[PDB]
Image (cartoon, rainbow, N blue to C red; front, side):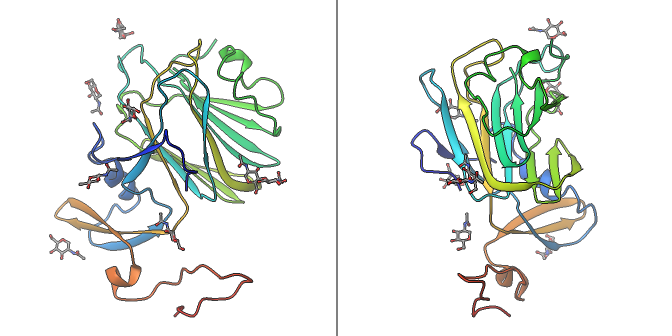
Length: 258
Ligand SMILES: *[C@@H]1O[C@H](CO)[C@@H](O[C@@H]2O[C@H](CO)[C@@H](O)[C@H](O)[C@H]2NC(C)=O)[C@H](O)[C@H]1NC(C)=O
Ligand SMILES: *[C@@H]1O[C@H](CO)[C@@H](O)[C@H](O)[C@H]1NC(C)=O
Ligand SMILES: *[C@@H]1O[C@H](CO)[C@@H](O)[C@H](O)[C@H]1NC(C)=O
Ligand SMILES: *[C@@H]1O[C@H](CO)[C@@H](O)[C@H](O)[C@H]1NC(C)=O
Ligand SMILES: *[C@@H]1O[C@H](CO)[C@@H](O)[C@H](O)[C@H]1NC(C)=O
Ligand SMILES: *[C@@H]1O[C@H](CO)[C@@H](O)[C@H](O)[C@H]1NC(C)=O
Ligand SMILES: *[C@@H]1O[C@H](CO)[C@@H](O)[C@H](O)[C@H]1NC(C)=O
């Protein structure tokens, strides 16, 4: 899903600090009942990508042909009061509207996150993270500040999914929906490392993953205990075929369909 880069290495999301149940809480967000059920969707996997640079130069990463983008952070320093932030900036392209999400390190108190809805393709990644907080998403672009919860201590997975009619943002354990008709290009550009500035601090404490395939998870709720298991094949987990398929070149149903 990510272009081959030497900086970007893999990593086990569940093996990191404070990430024991990072995916379990996300999977059971909607299934609040008792029993086992097989769900499908653009769900994150266990192996994500960590990308860092020893130097203080500006680096970029590209995710292509993806449908959802998830990321997680580390525990904030002094989260109770003056929380210390770790900067990040990822841009989802589209026409005629594109969305830039930037978490910082004039600005309202504790509102580390900013969302910039812009209609201009020329986005300056070497100047957005170098100016003041009041001169970032100024002008005709729509600026929406938002406060990432520091008390969560990075134990909640953040995510963004989109389509041509609806955009869903998962923050903490809450999913928010926005209705907008926009032609998305299904690629995301992420700027993970740059020189330190007033708003940007040189660090690397972000994991991240892009999901493009239809992932299947079996969920079991036994006496209040919640367990999840990934399925590489729907038929193997359920004993029955699935209706999701990828049409071949020219728009032809594959011969293996049921
Ligand atoms: C994201 O995908 C879109 C859609 O494919 C890309 O836009 C096209 O890019 C190609 C080159 O890859 C150009 O020849 C086309 O003219 C572009 N079309 C439009 C309508 O702009 C876009 O470049 C991709 N973005 C990134 C950052 O890779
Ligand atoms: C994740 O842990 C497993 C063992 O549980 C190990 O084999 C694998 O290499 C780890 N993956 C990464 C990306 O470190
Ligand atoms: C943490 O924040 C509190 C509340 O603002 C503050 O009193 C305290 O000094 C901070 N601790 C630090 C910066 O180590
Ligand atoms: C986050 O960490 C702080 C400091 O250790 C702790 O007081 C707080 O309860 C934690 N929040 C959680 C675990 O939700
Ligand atoms: C990513 O890797 C860097 C070294 O390249 C390391 O310092 C950093 O802690 C890693 N990030 C996470 C979230 O594990
Ligand atoms: C997604 O599905 C395609 C089907 O061709 C497969 O080749 C690819 O490996 C899958 N990707 C992942 C991450 O499972
Ligand atoms: C769910 O868990 C219970 C208790 O461990 C087990 O008996 C049952 O077989 C599980 N169901 C599925 C579908 O895996």
